[PDB]
Length: 241
Length: 278
Image (cartoon, rainbow over all chains, first blue to last red; front, side, top):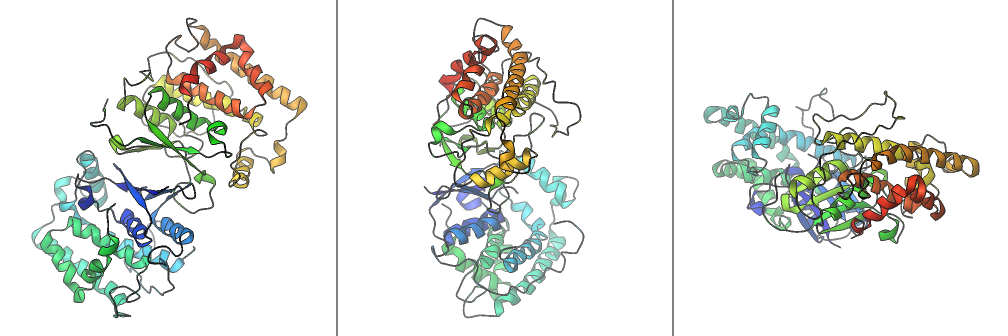
């Protein structure tokens, strides 16, 4: 009867090392709904998939899983994943050339948040917790992808890394403005959480796992510590079970 | 071979839900290949019967069969999928699943799924023009070609099965619409083939089975292609026979069982020890 949740395998203390942003959106959402589930770890995306035996359904992709959970369990747990709100945010470095319903303001936010965080993800490389079974192959994918010639080329350090942290800070400065509409609480809607906060929280989990501790301490504290406080507020939905 | 390091949680096998009494109506041919292969290897597993995601109104990313790594072509649907926790593996194609089971559990159960053999069979109605998903390099290339040709030979007679197809009632209408599209007809009742057209289709089916039966004459010491030694190539045929067994009238199934000196009835009978629905 419990839900089966398919996540990406990382280095053996998997409860503390798992860090793929899209499966973390679904984990946060399932905990938000307080549904019973167990995690199946798969080695190397296609990979947020759940099986819900309550409806004999197999659902892939994190956004569609979140729509499915809201439609199937509208009132479970903390309640509504998609409360009405205006998510007035565009990542202006999307551009208009490199190719690509329901809750379209959330679907758009998800696309813009993913684009904004993914462009800073060369910062996570030195700390990525490879599953040693998939390590050589995963390093190769990361290489084909950052457009470097080999794995040693990702060594970005010293001055060049500060410039990367700086650009990460500017991106987060523009995103922080959305958290100033309602400062009665740490979320976008103040004290009420939504799937839009979980989207950001999932990316914050990746950074917490993969960044040097001193660098996470800055990220946590930038822009009046808005993301640090969002992170702390989402801990209650962050159980790895 | 990479055997697993432990002995862990059981394999999860995702199969296509058919009409309520599911242990007796399940009939999808590609999932039956995987079931026969798991039973051949004698592995523990449980089945999750799910509605077919390919036809489901639920939006998601599981709508097309994955690419095949070790052979040309693809399965018809997403749904032969296994999760093997012993190796953190999620495998979504009947032929890749059988290759996986042979590399991971090479001596378990009845033993080798891919003993060397020539499988000299061509379905002559393939033609030469239809585009095909192509693998970079195939494992067990005689078996990879046999899999493609056996699917084509049986799938072209599958209008014989529509009247008896055991629809899960929750998905009957969406499944019927997909069959109507894949069959090139305008509506569900266009599939009605009765009396004279059904007999011609049965003669065609018998002609096809007659060419395939020649391969079972090369070793008469037993009912399998290699006589007393079974292989994944027998399971491919046994899987398609199970579809036929569920969806044909019993009286037409007995024709299939007894034609060509009962070669396919003997194979069916010899595969029953691997046919448990668990």
